[PDB]
Each structure stands twice: as structure tokens, then as C-alpha cells.
Amino acid sequence: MEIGVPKEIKNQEFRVGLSPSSVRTLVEAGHTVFIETQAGIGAGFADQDYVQAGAQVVPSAKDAWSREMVVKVKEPLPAEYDLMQKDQLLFTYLHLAAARELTEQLMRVGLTAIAYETVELPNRSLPLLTPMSIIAGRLSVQFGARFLERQQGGRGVLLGGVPGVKPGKVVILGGGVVGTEAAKMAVGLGAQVQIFDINVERLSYLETLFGSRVELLYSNSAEIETAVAEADLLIGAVLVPGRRAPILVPASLVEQMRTGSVIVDVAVDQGGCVETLHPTSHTQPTYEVFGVVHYGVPNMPGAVPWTATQALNNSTLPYVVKLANQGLKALETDDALAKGLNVQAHRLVHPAVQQVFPDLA
Amino acid sequence: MEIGVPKEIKNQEFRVGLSPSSVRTLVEAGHTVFIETQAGIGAGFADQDYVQAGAQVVPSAKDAWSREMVVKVKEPLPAEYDLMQKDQLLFTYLHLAAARELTEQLMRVGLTAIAYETVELPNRSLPLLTPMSIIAGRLSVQFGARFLERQQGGRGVLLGGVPGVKPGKVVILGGGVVGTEAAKMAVGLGAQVQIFDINVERLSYLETLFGSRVELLYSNSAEIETAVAEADLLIGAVLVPGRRAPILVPASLVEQMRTGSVIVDVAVDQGGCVETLHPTSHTQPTYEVFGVVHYGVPNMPGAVPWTATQALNNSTLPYVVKLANQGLKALETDDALAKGLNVQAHRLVHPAVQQVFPDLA
Amino acid sequence: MEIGVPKEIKNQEFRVGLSPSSVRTLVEAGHTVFIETQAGIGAGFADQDYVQAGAQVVPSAKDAWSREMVVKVKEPLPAEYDLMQKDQLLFTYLHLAAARELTEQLMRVGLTAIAYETVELPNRSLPLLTPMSIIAGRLSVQFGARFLERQQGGRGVLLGGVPGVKPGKVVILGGGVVGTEAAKMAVGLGAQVQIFDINVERLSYLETLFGSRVELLYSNSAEIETAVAEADLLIGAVLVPGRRAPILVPASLVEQMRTGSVIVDVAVDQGGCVETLHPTSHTQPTYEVFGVVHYGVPNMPGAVPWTATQALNNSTLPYVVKLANQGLKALETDDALAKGLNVQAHRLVHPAVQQVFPDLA
Amino acid sequence: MEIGVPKEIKNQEFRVGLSPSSVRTLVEAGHTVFIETQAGIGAGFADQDYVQAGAQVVPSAKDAWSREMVVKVKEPLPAEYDLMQKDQLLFTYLHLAAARELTEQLMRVGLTAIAYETVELPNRSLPLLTPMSIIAGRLSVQFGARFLERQQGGRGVLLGGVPGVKPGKVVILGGGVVGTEAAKMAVGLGAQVQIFDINVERLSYLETLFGSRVELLYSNSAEIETAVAEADLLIGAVLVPGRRAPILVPASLVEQMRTGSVIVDVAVDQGGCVETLHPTSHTQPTYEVFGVVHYGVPNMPGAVPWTATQALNNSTLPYVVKLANQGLKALETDDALAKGLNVQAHRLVHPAVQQVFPDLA
Amino acid sequence: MEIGVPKEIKNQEFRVGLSPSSVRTLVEAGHTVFIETQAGIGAGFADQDYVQAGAQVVPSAKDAWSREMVVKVKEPLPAEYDLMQKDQLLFTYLHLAAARELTEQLMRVGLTAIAYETVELPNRSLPLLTPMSIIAGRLSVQFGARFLERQQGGRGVLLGGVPGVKPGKVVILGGGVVGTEAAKMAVGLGAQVQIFDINVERLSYLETLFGSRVELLYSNSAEIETAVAEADLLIGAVLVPGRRAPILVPASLVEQMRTGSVIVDVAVDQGGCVETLHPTSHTQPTYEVFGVVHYGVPNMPGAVPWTATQALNNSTLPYVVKLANQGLKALETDDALAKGLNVQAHRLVHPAVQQVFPDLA
């Protein structure tokens, strides 16, 4: 089939729908791929890299959008509304429950739109989100370290300390994928680490990963208050993937933290467990409240497009290939894919999105 | 004795001569300490913290400089020239071989000036520099990670990668203290690590620290060329503490690196092993050459004043106390201290500095 | 019941159906065991060892075959065809889908034949093969090391290297049981290790075992080509247990490897992922193609009969006992056992074998 | 030579001068050994064990003391004063600076007495004490755990905690051999561990042992106060081997500890760094002060005589053999041994003991 | 709802039904809690601690029992029979299959009694027992170490040994939760460890925890005999949670052990795998048989009430809250809870208990 890859135009988005390795695989399966020139450049893939893989490099977005299958990272933007076509297959991150107009837009056109974030397994795991969650957990500590530096606003604490000097204290709220990846990085830098979670089974599993190197604590208000008050870096890792997390950290608690301490909440764009934290922009990524630095820039994985693009592709790939092969039938052969279907033939098919736009159903 | 601690006035210097814990110890020995208000604030120590320790908090630098012993971090600046007094003991980092005027200045006044950086052990180890070297090694990786981020200029590579994706490659030139601390952090983030050194004994010792987790390679031009060409992060850790390092990395080699790769050289302000690297300012910390990001801001430990101040104090402390107790006699009881003596009674006593200002001798 | 254990007569087969410890357990359950003298000797078990356990040591194979249950390692050979009896229970590795005559033979006689390799759990795991797979993964590295030695044909590379010198590079294709056991040994010798697999979940699980010590890469043609070209030891660990694996390594790729590199494919006797690799004999275990050493001797676990016999028994034991107790009813109490049934009462019962000899059904 | 080994008669002393393995070695060198029946029994060595080694088992102490060389663990007691002979070589732990009468006693008789505890190397290391120090460090945590149990008096805290629950906090004062061995055990049980020491080099070395798993802190009054106040188990490991340690822990600090916390000071019989701690008896090993349990039974290694006897012998052995071979000349061939000499020919030769009994010199 | 917490009156029981943190959570949910003064004291929780959490501290047990919900640790004792009320919800460890009278008693009164130990998941896991099992595994080694000390009765062996001396040998029978936690502690002390189990899958899983540090052996009589004969510490960890374990260790085997060896069987109060072992009292916790020390005090977790109370609460908490909220309906919303129901409205509802008191049904 013909597959097109337009350049991402969303602000600060540097990832790309398909990497050169992915292209090569698709091509080896008899498919042909068209990629807009410069599409991979922000992720470190030059057009030649695409050429060696078997892609035809196209000079314009129009040329990339005019294909039977469009594989992207972000949702289409208004500027691209007129590039979409009736019988297309669109595969990318959509987040329709937050975009009425886009939803309507896709409905008008008639194409079938499959969202990465809804492709779901029997376990109710979302295989196409996880890669990004892992990266976000790892970056949280990298960012946090940077903001604990004096010139960046923090108290000027080295996470690992040095022999003879106290190491930094990292408190992680949430013991899932994100919190686990964050603990790995924090332990790697030599920090003292505490992870809180309400699921003892999870706490038990974590002990098999970390042994006695990390403190594994049950999430109760009492212990949370004490820990947080002593934290240099507090990481919110309760990513409740539909609706918002409860407040585990109220402003009153934030007021009790040391000046120069830093807070990072991976759940920022969805709603965090930290009362005081809201989204920020790249130009002004942090702000203070009670002398405590808040970092609220969303989509952390966008900072490492080379790594993120491959991680995503490693997971989307098998789906892209199925779609390329079986076209629409793949949705009847693949339950996960079937679950990813959001819009088709002008109808809004996704149950969760209907629930949001009940009058759109 | 009376000991004064003025606030550091050098630009971007946030450390302080004595921490509250140090003060407390000095006070418990019968000594009295005067500290300029706000002196500890950049390092996270409030005046009250000094008060609880036994210090008298002074409103002005004059009040801090007017003491028998002045304990600082950086060298005195012109602005402070008129605050110095004839019979003072001055203990701080001086670096006289780079400051004719300061040297002359100290000579005029007549005080005795002891430099942290020359206090030397029989082993020719410099116990008062090491703490900073350790911190610098650890920060090199923290900074390097930040600059590999796309928005910061790098190719956008996550050092640790994610299962299924290549981790970042960190190449470290120099297997001493600095390079060893850097390898610890890089391994902690999950990177693939190579350390080069010309001393096999050192390489052997490093294997006892890292086992087979890190590649331990003899420094030969041939291997260096290959490694460097594949590096995401290259760290120069050849800190030859008097005079400059040889070029291990010529521009021709830099031209061979991938675009978005990053270079950090801990030896920048003294002269690195990387041809293309020069010092930069805080306002413009990096620059590109061949698409390779160069970070050249010096004094990395200044980014973590809370941690750095304690680390320094842990080492200077026993010397400060000796001086406070025995005053000038300590130089006849302590050989290391004796070696730290740079200027006294208008004479330039330091052999290495004489060699620099042979007409000053 | 009476259970007999004949000596294995297949060439180079040194294992034995039951070890002394197993015998002892069977005897303690009221069963009586007859073992042909010297049967255990190749595995390091002397007849006395069998005597102390409660076995009656028999002077001839006839005496061992004349029992209600025969427990063996390999399939019966023609020489033994006349030793089999009508109402016997035979339990051993059969591999009928490769032996028409044996299959017919067992059909003529009428005995019931249970194959180790088809006893299957609900998970479709084959509990009686796994023990051998684990051993094979571990040996792959042991053999590979031996063939990288100059006198053995390889380039003469020490896997672990020595501080200052590059370690060997081991590339493992397949992240399942076999590949995982191989990585354990390779890491143990100090090699640089890469594992490729197409299942990210598996890659993720592997990270919990190895942390960042091993490179965990998604199997894509592009990455495979690069890795393999740099390998000292390439290990094929894609054991697709029914039908053959796809070629992950074509001759063209082999031609790109360094001279003296070595290839070991655990899937050799079934069909490997390496184009150029075929089975070899003990007398001439390897051959070169493009200066690359190929090792193709099958049944690697046969090299360590002492270890292999116990490993097998630890798994077969509970089944042997059930059979001894409940005789044929055990097949109605045990689903796994039921699945192991291949031939009974002259009929070919195994669905997969029927499919092979559709006219035998 | 003839060597005798009397049974230790000191209360609660179960160790023995020579183990069976040692005997065997001595015998293989042409020497003959006489051991009092039951001498090894408290350490787990029966007379037969001595017989198989080549010893002649003697029925009485008299028979053991009547030899040219007497090898013991503890100092001779009054009861044995009349068993000593004029030209004997006595080798055991003496501690003369604490026993005027014993000293006089040995002077009267005229024998030559070599003390284990003074045999000294050029490094001023005491090779024959170290084995016991290592054991004492390891036991400190074992005892401490037992006293944190509710029925034993402590608050009832499990050192390692369980996933979801806070682990115990162990604070160790002193980073030498003893403190290091204690940290090893505490980390092994899963506790949170802090080690304090005033030597940064030592702290640095400790990081090579423990990585970031243990907190390595410079000993300053301020940090000490905080840490100790939060401790479940405080271990005094400042063993200043001649004269007493300074008080690092004053009663005022002890009053600040939690009720049920436990203190163990390895320096008890010499003088600890904990104000409130004094020696206790086996019958009443602990006592409370401020609700804090104090354990003050000395000679911890006596609890594991089997392990302690071998550890000691491994170190004394080469000396015993030298003495057996060269008799008194060994003191002119061995400087360490020469330093072990305390009394000879009625004269008190040991410089440090003279200093104690200046009128004995 | 009103929830009462009486003080545990069973002998040597120091735990408490709810900790202060738990109280605080319950109170934050609108519930009110009454706790008998001194109830938490044995676990280290003072009444004030309960006051700060929101509890009303009651002066008498009567006042604590007079509530709609009673949350305890142990079963009610006769002394409390008259404190129980008709419509109460009772939640604690009951063990009715061992107490006819208690069972009858609860039947008379009419309350609904939910047993911690029967609340069961679909997996047939008993989430409210596990916490105690983990603690018991960890303590087994702590106790065992204490009894290997000479003064305590053992041969006087240090588990970890010292460099140059044999470490202790710990043999663990059973590779489940208990045996696994025990191995963790034994390895932590430096002992040589062997774990036996009959489930190879479990053995395989254990290798992922311990690597090659521990010997993982299949449980067969032959290997068991050898291992046990060489053991310093034998730990019975076959906790078959309904009915008794088989004898893995017969007296004949015990007679073969070394004198001073120690045996601990976690299954003592239910029936162990060690023939010779029976329960003992706190006043006389051990006894010898063949010179082998037997420790038979039950309920090991009672030794660490502070740790045990929290561990238990972390698991019971979510159930306590459900009950407080939904009262009896929770049994129709929660299957696990439903399974915990033992007695209600005068009827004996628990299937397993009926089976025991078939005439009680």
C-alpha cells in the first residue's frame, strides 16, 4: 500500500511517524512509502537515510497526505484539515475527547481514524502509550536534577551527594511504570529514594527490582506528609490514564517543603496529585510557589525525539504493517486495533469519546 | 580566635567559606566567628542557621574582613582590596599564578595568604581540590544529558535508551577521579560507557569498581578515533593540575562526530584535551562547531552550592581549626599547610608562583 | 509397578532414563526398578549407586525392556525393535514426525508411547523440553568461547578481554529461554552483549534481569545487519519448536562478518535463522564459510550427561510416578500427560503426527 | 618443640589456643603438642579430633602447662600461677597494662611472655587483634537485632522492614574495620544505614565498598545529633586501641532517642563514645536509661568460639610455628614478634607497659 | 461508623488492631474510632499518637467493645465473652477450626465475624496472612543466628564467617514466600545457602532473584539427607496453610546433624516437616534432641509488634474502610470479604469450619 509521512507541524514536536528502519521493513513487505522532505530531521534522520531505506522523499505535505495511509505522531491541525482525504486510514495520537472540532472535522471528511492511545489489549494495557510513559519516568529525574541547580532556581543540591555529604532525597508518588523508571534513574544518580504506592503487591514486586536500596512505603496521608516535607525532588507519577488523580499533595503540604525543592508531575496535562502544579510553556518552564520550583512542561518525551521515535515505532510497527497488508480487515482480525478505531465513515465509533460528545454519537 | 566570613561577591559564586555545622565546631573550640549577613543564603544557609550555631552575624563585609582570619571560597577582588589588613590570615582559593595584581596586592598589605589549592600531602595529593573534582565529574554527565535534549541543541538522545532502543554512548577521556565519578553517573543513567586512560594499573583498579559493565581501554590514537566518532557524549577528564593537557581530540576528529553530539571538558579553564573547546559564559554556555555542541562554562561545582560548601568544609575544617588554635605555628607543625603558604610579610613564598613571577621573588 | 531402564545405545548418548535419586523415590513408592548394568555409567552413576537406591541391576537390555514401563532418554532404535512388548508403557523423547518407520513400528507392536516433548501444559509450555533448552543456552557460549581460540579455528579472542583491551562482542538472536541463558553466560565471562527480539514485552522483562548491562534491541533487519557485522560470536536462539525459523542471517550477511568469528545456532537440527549453518558431526564439528567458523553439532546437552540427566529427571519424575501409580488412568487425570500420548493400541493418536502421516491416521 | 594447650578456665571463655587443623600443621613440622582433655570442646573440637591431628591428649592442666611453649587465648589466672615454669614461652592475650599482679607474677617466674595484642607491623597494624575486631563488628548487628525485639526490651522493630513498611535505621559511629563489618551486616538485613567518620579518605574508600546504598557522613556534632535522635540501633565503633574514645554521644543526646532504641558499643571494656554505656554481665546483659536499651557485655567474639578460634589461629599460626622452630631467636628475625615481647627473664620489656608501671621497669 | 479497638489481652501479644496512621485515614473518611488506653503501647504507639490522629481514647475495654465494629489482631478470649454484642461486626484473626467454644460463643451472640485468615482472592491467595508470613521468614534467620551462639546453646558459629574461615550453612526446606524471605536474610549475613523445593518453576523464579548466589535444589530424599547432615541452621518453610506438611526431616535424619546445629520450623503450630520439633514456650523456647537445638516458639512476628502492626494494617486497611462504609453490603460487593465471613446471625457460614464442626452447621 502507499503510506505517507508528513512532517510534524505542531510546535516543538520533533518526532516523526516512521523511522528509516521502519521504512525499510515496510518496503521489504511490498509497500511504498512517501515521506515529506525534512520530516525526520528533528529526530536525527536525514532524507538520504530515508532514501537508502526505500522511501520516496516528497517535497510537500500535500504529497505526503495524499496517501491511503497516513502515519503520524500528533493529531492533525487545522492547517492540515484540507489535506485530508475521504478514504484514508489515519494512525496517530488523537486525544479526541479533548478536541470537539478535530472530532467533527474527521467526521466530515469520512476517513477512518485509529488512535495510538486507544489500541488496547485484553489486559486493558495500552501498548502504544507505554513507550512514552517509560521515557517520561526516566526524564523526570533528569529534569529534576537540572532544576535543583542553583542557577536554574533550586537549592543547589547534587542528587548523589559526595562521600561525607548527604545525598538528595527523591520522593516518588506512584509505583507504576512511570514511578519505577524514575526510581531507576534516581538510584543511578545515587540519591536516597522513597516510592509510595497503595498497592502492596506492587510494592512487593518493586522489592524484587530494587532489593533494600529504595524505601517502599504504603501511601497513607501521614507518611506522605513527613516524606514530602523532607524532599529535595518530588515526582508525581500517578498517571490515571482517563480521568484525573486525587490530590496527594495539597498546597498546605507544599508550603511545608524546603525552599529550592523541586516538583515534577508527570500527570500535569491530565491533572496531577499536586495541588499547586499547572502546565507551563517552554519559554517559561517553571514557576515558584512558596519558594518551591514547579516544572510543568508537558510531553517530556519530546525532548529526546531520536530515542522517542524509535521507541514508538518499535511498538506501532507491527500494527502499521497489518494495516498496510489487510487494510480495513485488520480490524476484524485484531481486537486491539479494533479498539483503536475512533472515527469511520462519518461516525464517531469510540465508546469513550461518544460518552464525551454524546450528541456526536 | 576571631574568624570572619564575608559574603562571596564574585559573579555567580554562591558558595560560602563556612557552613553552619562548621561554625558550630569552631565555636565549640573557643573561637568566635563573624559572618556577613546573607553570606550563606546562596548555599541555602540562613543567618538564623548561623545564629543557632554560635556565630555573630555582621551587617557588612568590612565587619567580616576586619578579623584575624578570613575564610573564603574565591580570591579577593579589587573591590575588597581596601578591606584587607596587615596581620591577617587569609585562607581561600587564590590561583596566584594567574593574577599578578592580586599577588602584588597581597604583597603590599603584608598578610599571610594560604591557598586551598596548594595545601599538599606527601603523596602530592591536593586534599582541598579533590572534593571539587569529584563534584565536577558527577556534574559532567548531568550537564551532558541536558544538552543532548533536542530543545537544548543536541540530537535528542536519552542516555539510558529504553528496552528495544540503543542507549547513548559516553566516551570518557581520563580514568582518574574526575573520569571515574563521571563513569559512575553515566552507568547510573544506563548509558554504554568507555573510559580511556594511559595507565594500565589505573585501568585495572577501575575494573574492581565497575566489573565488566564499562569498557576499559588504553589510550591510543587509533582507538580514540573510532570511539569518539561514535560518541553521543564526550567527556574530557584529563585534569593535569598545573599545566595543560595534550590534545587527544583535534578538530579533525570533532568534524567526524555525529551532529547533535555533545562535548564537555572538565579541564576547560586550564586547557582541555579537545582542540575546539574554549570557555563560555553562563548566558551563552554552549556553541556549535560542525554541528557538535560545546559546553564550556567553568567551575561546574558552583551549580550545587549547598552540596559543594559542605564538601569543601569537610576537608578544610581540620585546617581551619589548626590555624585558629596555633595561628602561624601551625605551619611548622603541618607540612601540608606549610605548602599552602603563598604570601607572607610582603614576600611571595610559593615556589611555583615565584617561577611565574620570577621578578616578584 | 515394574519399571525398566535400558542403557542408551544411540551414538554419543550418555544420559540415562533415571538417576539414582529418582530410583530411590520410585522404590519408596512401592515400585520396583530394573536397570541394565552400565546404563548410568556415561552420566557418572555406577551400578552400586543404583543398588544403594533400591534398583535391581539387570545384565541385559532384554531384561530392562521386558518391563511394564520403560523409561528412556532417546527413541528406540531398530536394534531394539524386537525387545518391545505389546502392553508396555514407553516414555522417552520420540520425535515421531521425523520417523515414519519408528512410528509404524510402535503401531505394529501396540504399546502405548508417551513422548516427553509433547507433554503440554495449558500455557502450551512443554515442561519436559525446557530443561534441555536451558542447558543448550548455557553451553552455546561455552562452545563459542572454545571456537574463538586460535588453535580451534577462531580469531583468538578472549570474551572478557582484559582491562585496557576490547572485550568480545556476543550477538544473540532471540530473547526467549535459550537466548536468555546464553546472555547470562556471556555476561558472566565479561563480554559485550546484545540480544535481539521482536517482542518488546520480552525485552522489557529482560531488563529486569540484566539492568543496563546488556543491549536490548528490537529485531529489525537494519540493526541486525550492523550488529552481526561487528560480532565475534553470533548465537542463533530462535527455537520455533514445531516448524523452522526465518532467516535472520543470510549468507550475504555472513560474508560481512570478520574472519575468525564464530556462529552457533541452537536451532540447527530443526532449521536455524542463519542461512549458512547446517548440522555437522562430532568428528568434524565445525566448518568455515567466508572465514567464519560454523559449529553445527546438535544436541548440545549431551556434552554434560551428569547435569542433563538430573535436570531431565527433576521434570519427568512426577510424571513417571503418576504413571507408575495409576498406569493408563493417569492420562484421564492428567491433561499434560494425555497430550504426551502419541501411539496406543496400534493407533497413531497424536494430532500433530497424524497431520504428518495423514495416511497413518 | 613441645607445645601445650591447657583448657581456658576464664568464665565464659570457650575458645581454645589451637584448633585441630593448627595442631596438624605443627605436628607436620616435627613438633609435638599436648592438649588438655576437653580443651576444645566449647569451640566444637572433640579430643578425637585432636587425636586424628597428631596431638597427645593430656588429662590435666598441669600436663599442658609443663611444656616449653604454652599457647592460650586469655591471660593466666591466679589459679594457674603455680603451673607456670621458669623457661617457658607464653603466647596469649595478656593485657598487662591492666593487671599489675599478673605482670608481677610473670616477672617472678622468669618466663618470656609474648602478648597477641602487641605483635605489631611496621604499619602499626596489630594483626592478631583484627580477626576479633571483624567478628565483633559483625556481631554488633546480630545482638542489636535481638534487642530491638519486644520480648527482649526494644521497640519491636524488624531491621529490614517489609515492602510498604519503614526499615530500621542503623547509625554507626566510626568507619574503620569494626564499623565497616557492622555496616555489611546491617545492609544485609535490609536496614537503612548511616556511617559517620572524621576521615574523608576513609569515607571515600567506603563508597567503593557500598556504592550509594549506605549514607556516608562526616562526623560533626550537628549531624550526629540529628542522626542519633532518629536511630533504632546505634553502634559505637570507635575503637581507639590504647586509650579511650571521646564522647560522641552524651547522655543529653541519649535522652533524645526513641524509647526501645538500642545501643551497642564495641569499645565498652576500653571506654566508649557513648556517655551512658558501661559494662554489664552475661546474667544481666542490658539496662535502660531513658527507655533506651543498653547492651554492655564485653568480648562479643566469645559468642562464636568455633568461628573465633579458627579466625585467631589463621593469624597466630605462622607465629606459633616460627617460635616452635627458632625458639627465642625468632624475636631477632621477626620485628612484629619482637614487639609482642612483654616480659622476659624477670624484666618488664614492653615500653607501653613500663609507662604504666614505671616502677616496674 | 463507630469502630472500637480494645487492647490485646492474649499473653505476649503486643500488636494492636489499628495503628495511628490507619486511624487517621478512617477518621478522614467520616468514621469515628474509639481505642482503649494503652492499646498501642506494646507496638510503640502512645495514646497521644492516637489523639493526634482523631481517635477518642477510651478508659476501658468495655468502651472499646461496645462499638459496631471491632477491629483486633487475636481471637476474643473467654474474659471478653461478655463484652461482645449482638449486632457487631468483628474483624480479626479467628482460627475457628481450632476453637469449638469460641465458635459456639460467637454463634450464641449472633454478631458477624470476619476472619483475616480466610479473606481470599480468586487466586486462592490469602492477602491478610502474607504480611505475617514475610516477617516470619525474615525472623527465622535472626532467631537461628542467636541460637547458634555458644551461650545460647549452639555450636558458636558466625553465619557469615570471616575471610579465611568457613561461613555457616543454612538449609531451607520450602521455596515459597517464607523460604524466600529467609534466604534473603541468610544471604545478607553472608551464609552459604541451599533452598529445596519440589516445584521447578519456583526454583526457576528464585534464580531470577538470587542468580548463582544460592544453591537451588529439587526436593528429593537423597539430596535432603546429605544437605541436612551438613547444616548449621535448618529452616522448615513448608507452610501448607490448611493441613500439615509431610515429614521431610525424620528423627533419624536429625540424629545425623552436628551437635550445636539449630532447627527452626515456621510451620510449628500447624505441624512441621521436622519430626522432632514441637511448640515451646517463651520461658523455655528451645530444647535439645541429639545435641541439636530446637526452637519452637510460635507466632514469630509477635517479636516485632511495631513492624508487624503496620504491615498488617497496610493490608487490612482497605477492608476495614469498605466495611465501615458499606457495612454488611460490602460482602456482596467484595468476594474476598465474602470469603472471610465465618459466623453470622448465629449460623456458622464458613465451609471449611463447617467441615470441622459438621454438627455445628
Image (cartoon, coloured by chain):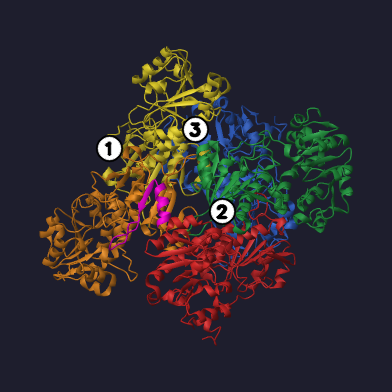
Chain colours: A green, B red, C blue, D orange, E yellow
Estimate the x, y position of residue B298 in percent, counting from the top left: 61, 67
In the figure, E41 relative to B134: above or below?
above
- Secondary structure found at label 1: strand
* Residue interval drawn in magenta: D221-248
Q: Chain of mark 3?
A: E
Seen in the image, is D205 located left or right of residue A157?
left
| Label 3 residue SS | helix
Left or right: B175, with D137 as reference point: right
Residue highlighted by disc 1: E288
Label disc, if present, on residue A188 of the rendered structure: 2
Q: Nearer the viewer, mark 2 or mark 3?
A: 3
Toward the bottom, the furthest residue is: B359
- Among numbered discs 1 and 3, the one appearing first in the sequence: 3
Residue B317, horizontal then vertical, whole percent: 44, 65
Residue E308 locus on image (x, y percent): 42, 35
Tell me the SS state at disc 2.
helix
Tags 1 and 3 touching, CB below 8 Å: no
Q: Are marks 2 and 3 in contact (CB under 8 Å)?
A: no
Kindly identify the amino acid type of the residue bearing the numbered disc 2.
Gly
Examine the structure image and report whether residue D285 is included in the region drawn in magenta.
Answer: no
Q: Give how far apart the Cα atoms at labels 2 and 1 are.
A: 49 Å
- Residue tagged by mark 3? E24
**Label 1 lies in what chain?**
E
Answer left or right for D307 relative to C290. Answer: left
Q: Nearer the viewer, residue B192 or B306?
A: B306
Q: Tell me the crowding category of disc 2: few under 14, some 14 to 19, or many 20 or more residues within 10 angstroms, Cα based.
A: some
- Residue D245 counted in the magenta span: yes
Viewer-side residue, D73 vs D292: D292
Measured in 3D between alpha carbons, the distance from the residue under mark 1 to the one under mark 3, in whole angstroms, is 48 Å
